[PDB]
Length: 51
Length: 51
Image 1 (spheres, chains in turn purple, red):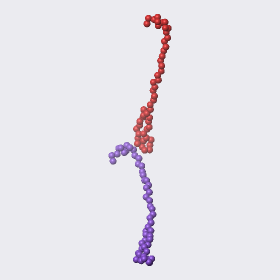
Image 2 (tube, each protein chain N blue to C red):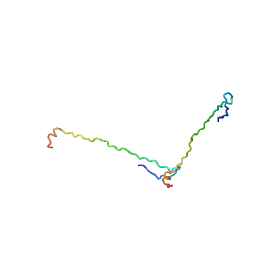
Image 3 (tube, one colour):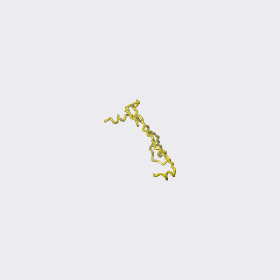
Image 4 (cartoon, rainbow over the protein chains, first blue to last red):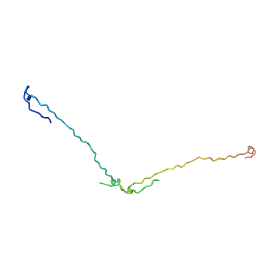
């Protein structure tokens, strides 16, 4: 995070000068990974079922 | 001719597996073979005969 400061009206004193400051960022990642299952069943069981 | 079966329902036991089968064909052939005869006679006998 940057930091600011209070500044006097002056053209000659050090308190007349606005501070410089930086802001910085870093990186985070979403990496997609696969989760899965296979459920085998007789075709006759699937054809027979009303539900 | 292909041969069928009654195929059970197990995912694990051999009674659950549909049997493989096999139609086949064969070749019959007409092969042309020659039947022949030569019948020789004297040119005078033809001339002297009534038929």
